[PDB]
Amino acid sequence: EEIKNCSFNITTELRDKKKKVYALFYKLDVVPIDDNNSYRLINCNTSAIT
Amino acid sequence: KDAETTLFCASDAKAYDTEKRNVWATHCCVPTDPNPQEIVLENVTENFNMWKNNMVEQMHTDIISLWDQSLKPCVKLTPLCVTLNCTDVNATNEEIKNCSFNITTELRDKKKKVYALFYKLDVVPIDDNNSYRLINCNTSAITQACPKVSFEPIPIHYCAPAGFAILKCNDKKFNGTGPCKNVSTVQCTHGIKPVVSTQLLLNGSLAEEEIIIRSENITNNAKTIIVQLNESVEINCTRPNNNTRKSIRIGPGQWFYATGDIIGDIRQAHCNISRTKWNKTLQQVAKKLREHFNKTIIFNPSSGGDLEITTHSFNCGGEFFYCNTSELFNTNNTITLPCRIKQIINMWQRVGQAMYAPPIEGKIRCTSNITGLLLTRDNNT
Amino acid sequence: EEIKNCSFNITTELRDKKKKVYALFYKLDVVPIDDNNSYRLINCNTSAIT
Amino acid sequence: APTFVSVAPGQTARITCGEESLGSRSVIWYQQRPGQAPSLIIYNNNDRPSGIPDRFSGSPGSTFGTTATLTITSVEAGDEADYYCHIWDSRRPTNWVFGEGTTLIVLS
Amino acid sequence: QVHLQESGPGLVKPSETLSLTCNVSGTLVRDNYWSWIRQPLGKQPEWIGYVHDSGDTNYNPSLKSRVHLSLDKSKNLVSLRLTGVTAADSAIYYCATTKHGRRIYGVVAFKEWFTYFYMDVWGKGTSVTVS
Ligand SMILES: *[C@@H]1O[C@H](CO)[C@@H](O[C@@H]2O[C@H](CO)[C@@H](O[C@@H]3O[C@H](CO[C@H]4O[C@H](CO[C@H]5O[C@H](CO)[C@@H](O)[C@H](O)[C@@H]5O)[C@@H](O)[C@H](O[C@H]5O[C@H](CO)[C@@H](O)[C@H](O)[C@@H]5O)[C@@H]4O)[C@@H](O)[C@H](O[C@H]4O[C@H](CO)[C@@H](O)[C@H](O)[C@@H]4O[C@H]4O[C@H](CO)[C@@H](O)[C@H](O)[C@@H]4O[C@H]4O[C@H](CO)[C@@H](O)[C@H](O)[C@@H]4O)[C@@H]3O)[C@H](O)[C@H]2NC(C)=O)[C@H](O)[C@H]1NC(C)=O
Ligand SMILES: *[C@@H]1O[C@H](CO)[C@@H](O[C@@H]2O[C@H](CO)[C@@H](O[C@@H]3O[C@H](CO[C@H]4O[C@H](CO)[C@@H](O)[C@H](O[C@H]5O[C@H](CO[C@H]6O[C@H](CO)[C@@H](O)[C@H](O)[C@@H]6O)[C@@H](O)[C@H](O)[C@@H]5O)[C@@H]4O)[C@@H](O)[C@H](O[C@H]4O[C@H](CO)[C@@H](O)[C@H](O)[C@@H]4O[C@H]4O[C@H](CO)[C@@H](O)[C@H](O)[C@@H]4O)[C@@H]3O)[C@H](O)[C@H]2NC(C)=O)[C@H](O)[C@H]1NC(C)=O
Ligand SMILES: *[C@@H]1O[C@H](CO)[C@@H](O[C@@H]2O[C@H](CO)[C@@H](O[C@@H]3O[C@H](CO[C@H]4O[C@H](CO[C@H]5O[C@H](CO)[C@@H](O)[C@H](O)[C@@H]5O)[C@@H](O)[C@H](O)[C@@H]4O)[C@@H](O)[C@H](O[C@H]4O[C@H](CO)[C@@H](O)[C@H](O)[C@@H]4O[C@H]4O[C@H](CO)[C@@H](O)[C@H](O)[C@@H]4O)[C@@H]3O)[C@H](O)[C@H]2NC(C)=O)[C@H](O)[C@H]1NC(C)=O
Ligand SMILES: *[C@@H]1O[C@H](CO)[C@@H](O[C@@H]2O[C@H](CO)[C@@H](O[C@@H]3O[C@H](CO)[C@@H](O)[C@H](O)[C@@H]3O)[C@H](O)[C@H]2NC(C)=O)[C@H](O)[C@H]1NC(C)=O
Ligand SMILES: *[C@@H]1O[C@H](CO)[C@@H](O[C@@H]2O[C@H](CO)[C@@H](O)[C@H](O)[C@H]2NC(C)=O)[C@H](O)[C@H]1NC(C)=O
Ligand SMILES: *[C@@H]1O[C@H](CO)[C@@H](O[C@@H]2O[C@H](CO)[C@@H](O)[C@H](O)[C@H]2NC(C)=O)[C@H](O)[C@H]1NC(C)=O
Ligand SMILES: *[C@@H]1O[C@H](CO)[C@@H](O[C@@H]2O[C@H](CO)[C@@H](O)[C@H](O)[C@H]2NC(C)=O)[C@H](O)[C@H]1NC(C)=O
Ligand SMILES: *[C@@H]1O[C@H](CO)[C@@H](O[C@@H]2O[C@H](CO)[C@@H](O)[C@H](O)[C@H]2NC(C)=O)[C@H](O)[C@H]1NC(C)=O
Ligand SMILES: *[C@@H]1O[C@H](CO)[C@@H](O[C@@H]2O[C@H](CO)[C@@H](O)[C@H](O)[C@H]2NC(C)=O)[C@H](O)[C@H]1NC(C)=O
Ligand SMILES: *[C@@H]1O[C@H](CO)[C@@H](O[C@@H]2O[C@H](CO)[C@@H](O)[C@H](O)[C@H]2NC(C)=O)[C@H](O)[C@H]1NC(C)=O
Ligand SMILES: *[C@@H]1O[C@H](CO)[C@@H](O[C@@H]2O[C@H](CO)[C@@H](O)[C@H](O)[C@H]2NC(C)=O)[C@H](O)[C@H]1NC(C)=O
Ligand SMILES: *[C@@H]1O[C@H](CO)[C@@H](O[C@@H]2O[C@H](CO)[C@@H](O)[C@H](O)[C@H]2NC(C)=O)[C@H](O)[C@H]1NC(C)=O
Ligand SMILES: *[C@@H]1O[C@H](CO)[C@@H](O[C@@H]2O[C@H](CO)[C@@H](O)[C@H](O)[C@H]2NC(C)=O)[C@H](O)[C@H]1NC(C)=O
Ligand SMILES: *[C@@H]1O[C@H](CO)[C@@H](O[C@@H]2O[C@H](CO)[C@@H](O)[C@H](O)[C@H]2NC(C)=O)[C@H](O)[C@H]1NC(C)=O
Ligand SMILES: *[C@@H]1O[C@H](CO)[C@@H](O)[C@H](O)[C@H]1NC(C)=O
Ligand SMILES: *[C@@H]1O[C@H](CO)[C@@H](O)[C@H](O)[C@H]1NC(C)=O
């Protein structure tokens, strides 16, 4: 419905490596990039999030 | 009436230039009175309490604040949290590792392969293979100590604002808390050197007649016992190998200072305490402690914890030493304590705020006075 | 003469991608790296530009 | 292996051997006349065993970045020989092989 | 004075064991360290190894697996044995007395020193070839 299970590539403490991790997001926080399963957070287009 | 207020920094000499930028010569600290007055108050009694004294909390706060401000504008070393390819240095047939890094240059499209030497204490293995990480990347970002800023202690006088006064206790045998009969008024305190150490107090003021033992509650094993000596014991410390400094660019005007090649022999850092002076001093401390317990007193090496508590941590020359004191708390020779040196530091238990101490070229020689001890307690002993 | 047409690889809002873009620069702001058509802005050697 | 020095009788010869030092060294020098077993000239940089004249004097082991040098002053015809050094450096493994020597040729 | 007189077969075959001796006269075999030196023709000499009492024996790592040294206290001889003889073992072999000293550069208590060795009395040596 409105909850999406998303995978990220996140830089770890050691800068040479990234880890693949998961998080759940509400649909209202996530905007599609493609027609395929490729999404962005809604803020990246406008602002940094604290 | 008793009061808690804001005191100000004052100094004796303005002999300090702007090249050294000593943090205790901030140029925001005022000169004190070159011919200070002191007024003896006759027929007065005043209750002093060193354990509830608010001047201590204020001094502590000022020092933490001063260090954070001094390091505020300096280079951050977060770009160094990269896999380090490390092998031992050619100190072969110990504690110094020769490590390779991939560092982004001023042009973002390129990285350069560079080398630096690190002390073992600053580097933690990732793998069982030759793959290491700096110890801070796991917890915190490192700020490089400013290469142009001295942290050498300068005596500071804490002086009262208008409407306030500082009372001084002149009873030679005053210990912890209680009345002082000889009381005088001053504008301010004597100069106090903000010397940082953990087992042996260095370069302080000696007791006038005898060893004075001060505690908040001498029957509480959880309290620190501060022992003020009436005679100093000298310590000679050194960093015997000749270091070089390698300047590595890590960004657009962002320089990292790495230890370069070691020239000549590779030798261990150490501190020298005369055996005869130590022996009489420690025995006199046991004798004086006895007056409060009536038991035979012995000393033991520390029980464990990280280096700041288990070793005699101190700064000298800008370098950070951790000396092993098991030979003290236990002939006519000299007691030579081996010492280790480390560059990645978390001062005042503030885990989360790491500092990197850049290398100092050449050799280091320190002379210091043991003026007191910080002791704790666990029988007819 | 003194105006150069330069191409850059710039990270976009989405961190996984870079876009190739163009800008014109005055010669006085650009220093060669190579003898080939490879240049750098004059400040990267000393400072960040606001 | 050997290199060469040409010295007129009475002149001072400078014989070098080994690479730049890293740490403190104790250099031992040996002299081999053709057909003979080699023998010791100096040990510990400057210590002559009895029987060796003071015209044979080495460089100190107290500095770094330099190479071992044996100075032979007033060279005599009897000093024609192959000179070898054995370098004991505090930052290197025991060197089990003597360094390549120098043939000192006295031009007599 | 001290005279060291070497002796051996002169010529040995590949894969044979070479056994050399050294007749020590003027000193007792357990009085000093002994060492063997090898000089391939035209080359600078190699230190094969050294032997002494109290177990203080060591060998050139390139030879170690094929070499044995010992002191004969009954005959006052120093022995050298090399197994697996090859072309590379053709050399002049010498028996020599070894003396030592210590170089101290740092704190003695931290072991900032090393032992160095030198060869004092040298014998005439023998020529050993292979074929
Ligand atoms: C905390 O406390 C601790 C403990 O107290 C302190 O630890 C001390 O740390 C220092 C660091 O410097 C160490 O210093 C070195 O000591 C060695 C050893 O010297 C002693 O032994 C020598 C040899 O012994 C002879 O006699 C014995 C007797 O049995 C015999 O067994 C042995 O075989 C031999 O025959 C003595 O000669 C020497 O005496 C000389 O020095 C004395 C110093 O005070 C002086 O009083 C005497 O009058 C005399 O002058 C002493 O007993 C030293 O060898 C070493 O110095 C050499 O090495 C350094 C580093 O490489 C170099 O810079 C120096 O220049 C020097 O190198 C020269 O001498 C070498 C000798 O082999 C030679 O090989 C070099 O080529 C070079 O030669 C030059 O001089 C010679 C002179 O003839 C000349 O001919 C050459 O041409 C050339 O010019 C250091 O002094 C301490 O040993 C150490 N102590 C202990 C117990 O660990 C610690 O420092 C303290 N820390 C603090 C912060 O205070
Ligand atoms: C890094 O390089 C350095 C040099 O660049 C290496 O330094 C030295 O290397 C030696 C090995 O080549 C080590 O030798 C070991 O010595 C042990 C015995 O103790 C000696 O060392 C101590 C150190 O203080 C001395 O005090 C001690 O004795 C002193 O006093 C003696 C008395 O002499 C009097 O009397 C005689 C007559 O008898 C007279 O001639 C004298 O003039 C005097 O009057 C004096 O003679 C001594 O010279 C000295 O002053 C000793 O010197 C041994 O027990 C060891 O033996 C075995 O274990 C080692 C472990 O590695 C093995 O390597 C070695 O091969 C031995 O192995 C066993 O198995 C093999 C199998 O083949 C057998 O062949 C062996 O026989 C044995 O069964 C060593 O001999 C020396 O200690 C070391 N120096 C230091 C400071 O460590 C250094 O070793 C090297 N680092 C590493 C990690 O290897
Ligand atoms: C308890 O108290 C004691 C006593 O105060 C503390 O011990 C002191 O600690 C000081 C800091 O570590 C140390 O000061 C350094 O000493 C070095 C050695 O100096 C020798 O030569 C001087 C010559 O003096 C003359 O020249 C100076 C130059 O300024 C004048 O100021 C003097 O008036 C004289 O004209 C002797 O006086 C000494 O006794 C020694 O023989 C100095 O080299 C060092 O200076 C360098 O580092 C400074 C760091 O701030 C820097 O400001 C200065 O400019 C020098 O730096 C130059 O050279 C380096 C070389 O690498 C280069 O990198 C720099 O870029 C620059 O070119 C300091 O002066 C005290 O000597 C020492 N006292 C004793 C008795 O040992 C003790 O620390 C304290 N306890 C604790 C725990 O803190
Ligand atoms: C460590 O403690 C010792 C004392 O145990 C301190 O030594 C003493 O230092 C004072 C200086 O504050 C010396 O006083 C003055 O010295 C000058 C020297 O010219 C002299 O002209 C003056 O008249 C006066 O004597 C004092 O004499 C000296 N004591 C001794 C025995 O030397 C030492 O300074 C302390 N600090 C360190 C780091 O060593
Ligand atoms: C970053 O994300 C990309 C995909 O978004 C990961 O690429 C995939 O990695 C798996 C690993 O087996 C491959 O099987 C896929 O075929 C890859 N996808 C593509 C399109 O090539 C990439 O591995 C992630 N990075 C990290 C460090 O995990
Ligand atoms: C990036 O931001 C812009 C606005 O700054 C978005 O533009 C509009 O976004 C609203 C949000 O729902 C849409 O309803 C409008 O239709 C968008 N405009 C147009 C012309 O479509 C833009 O869509 C954002 N990026 C993405 C991928 O949505
Ligand atoms: C009480 O304290 C005062 C200081 O507040 C002592 O007075 C000092 O005595 C020394 C003795 O030589 C003088 O050199 C100082 O100049 C005096 N200072 C002042 C401010 O007068 C006084 O001696 C102490 N009395 C007792 C009994 O301890
Ligand atoms: C850096 O890492 C490499 C491998 O992770 C270490 O080993 C070298 O690997 C290369 C690969 O071709 C070989 O050619 C070298 O010969 C290897 N070195 C050795 C000594 O065998 C390399 O040693 C590491 N360097 C450091 C400073 O740790
Ligand atoms: C970043 O570090 C890696 C290794 O940690 C470097 O990769 C090696 O590069 C050398 C160059 O010849 C190769 O021979 C090795 O085989 C590479 N190692 C591996 C595991 O592939 C890499 O080049 C460094 N980056 C930069 C810019 O120097
Ligand atoms: C990353 O940090 C954690 C703690 O924040 C480390 O965990 C402990 O570190 C101490 C340091 O010596 C070890 O003695 C403990 O044994 C560690 N815990 C465990 C369960 O082993 C952690 O080890 C750090 N990362 C690495 C690679 O050491
Ligand atoms: C200095 O030490 C003496 C003890 O020798 C302290 O005496 C106080 O004695 C009473 C007696 O009941 C205790 O209740 C107090 O707790 C003791 N005080 C302390 C701090 O333990 C004296 O107060 C101490 N301090 C001063 C400045 O005199
Ligand atoms: C610590 O170092 C000081 C000097 O830096 C030593 O003081 C010297 O001691 C010798 C002893 O004979 C005297 O001859 C010198 O004149 C003293 N020097 C000075 C400047 O007075 C002190 O003894 C050392 N302490 C230890 C424990 O070694
Ligand atoms: C970053 O810049 C590089 C060149 O500076 C681009 O690499 C070129 O990409 C084109 C695409 O077709 C290739 O045809 C060229 O051969 C590539 N050059 C080289 C030297 O390989 C790269 O694509 C740029 N990155 C992005 C995201 O545009
Ligand atoms: C990076 O900066 C340095 C100075 O910090 C530049 O060095 C000089 O730059 C001037 C500018 O015209 C030249 O005229 C000088 O000839 C340069 N020095 C030398 C020795 O050539 C340096 O050139 C800058 N990097 C680049 C690529 O310009
Ligand atoms: C304090 O130091 C002096 C120095 O002479 C000494 O005489 C006195 O005995 C010491 N105090 C004690 C309690 O030993
Ligand atoms: C130091 O303490 C240890 C504790 O095991 C003891 O064994 C050692 O003998 C003590 N050293 C001295 C000098 O008392």
Image (cartoon, coloured by chain):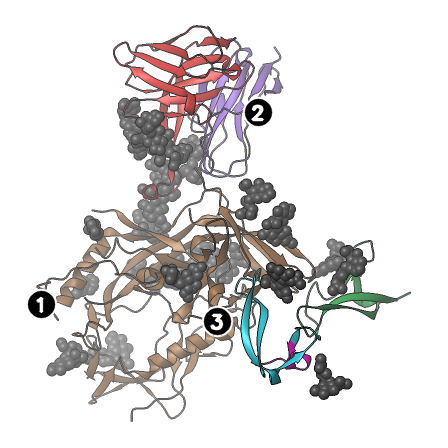
Chain colours: A cyan, B brown, C green, D purple, E red
Numbered disc 3: what chain? Answer: B
Q: Residue B211: x and y, percent? A: 20, 67
Residue at 58 percent across and 17 percent down: it is D104
E34 versus B347 height, above or below: above
Residue A45 lies in the magenta stretch: yes
- Whether residue A44 appears in this view of the structure is yes
Residue at 22 percent across and 77 percent down: it is B216
Numbered disc 2: what chain? Answer: D
Q: Nearer the viewer, residue B122 or B253?
A: B122
Type of amino acid at the residue the image marks with label 1:
Asn
Type of amino acid at the residue the image marks with label 3:
Val
- Tell me the tag on residue D14: 2
Mark 1 neighbour density, 10 Å: few (under 14) some (14–19) many (20 or more): few
Residue annotated with mark 1: B294
Q: Secondary structure at mark 3?
A: loop
Ligand 11 in which quarter:
bottom left
Residue B209 lies in the magenta stretch: no
Name of the residue lying farthest toward the front? A1
